[PDB]
Length: 219
Length: 219
Ligand SMILES: O=P(O)(O)CC[C@@H]1O[C@H](CP(=O)(O)O)[C@@H](O)[C@H](O)[C@H]1O
Ligand SMILES: O=P(O)(O)CC[C@H]1O[C@@H](CP(=O)(O)O)[C@H](O)[C@@H](O)[C@@H]1O
Ligand SMILES: [Mg+2]
Ligand SMILES: [Mg+2]
Image 1 (cartoon, rainbow over the protein chains, first blue to last red):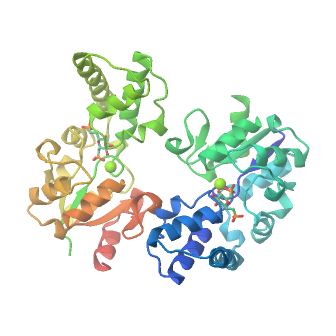
Image 2 (cartoon, rainbow over the protein chains, first blue to last red):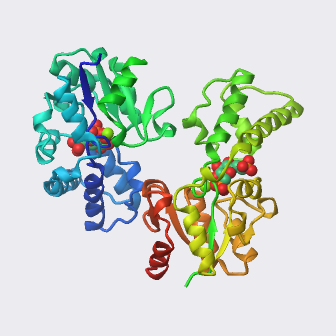
Image 3 (cartoon, rainbow over the protein chains, first blue to last red):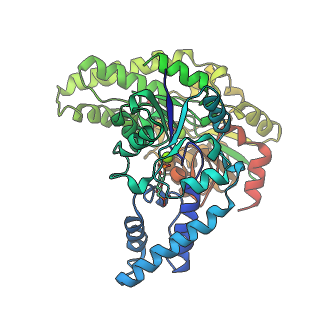
């Protein structure tokens, strides 16, 4: 019977994508480039700041100094951090608070397996700190998803092997990183995105202790 | 005020996409090709029967006689047609029937702008034919989505300019066809897929007569 659950943050617990998007939007407009819409920002999901910034510059063919490039990246980051001050318990995805409580009361370990450098602050803002047994530091992790490194650390830090764990992810890269860590992925989203070898729920309200017990029994 | 609503079928009124998938899968399973999952089926969405089969053959760099190519295409279409025999009013997306009635009783014209060769059949099976004043024949149009041809043809069929019409659609190419017809689009889905510049509802339950009216005003 699974001993831990390793939570993705963005797309499972909450939406950080929205704030990163407004942040890139504000910076693009601040400096006159158009065409940073939610469609275009599908290419700024996952990639680091350098890559994102290049793709926004590459839109108006703006040329910038190494000095200018560092500052713009920094004003995007200052933006992002200002905007996530708003985050409240109101921002938690359906079913998640009730899943965290059910897991805690069944003595199942709870770990965050997220690339957010803001994970600890976001879990405090949403008043979930008390549920989480460990937060994998993405700064202590050698490669991002689809490398399993983040899921292995999250497992190790609550004292379980990944093979004793379920991972919940929203992204195709995250599903891959769970599979390669040895954990059982349960997806949220569409099989068109995440694949049809793994069990997927349409939305997070379907992530129940009783559903996760059902899936563990049938692997 | 808008005089007509122009409806997509698949993704608005019901789901055909899933039976297509099953047919391409059961066909690929039979000829010994692997890798036809719902991820890959996303690349057949829009494509002709002919090119759909090619893309399944290209998965195994494989060729067959131009004669048996047509028997495969046929075997798959025969299979699709067997599977939609069970379509019923139970398969109509939420809000859609309530919307059709509200439109009718407000003397507002209702037309299918679908690429389905089986549109009329499906409408009978879902007992919607009575709500529909016209069905754009997709065989009688020069170019498929994202060309406007089908939304133009649908508007003309009920005696209005596209510019007097709202078009509801779930795909990026559909939205484009609606935009280039002169009609107002309202997407169902994700701005990440359909665009920032048009109004989008998360699902078909939000397509209310009252909501369409609010959008028609605010453009
Ligand atoms: O600037 P940061 O927030 O520190 C790191 C960037 C974001 O982190 C997310 C965390 P998760 O999905 O793994 O929870 C990823 O999904 C995004 O695609 C990624 O752009
Ligand atoms: O074989 P058929 O059913 O005759 C034609 C098949 C096409 O049907 C459309 C229905 P609609 O969305 O335009 O209503 C889908 O969007 C396409 O993805 C699909 O390839
Ligand atoms: Mg995520
Ligand atoms: Mg459609």
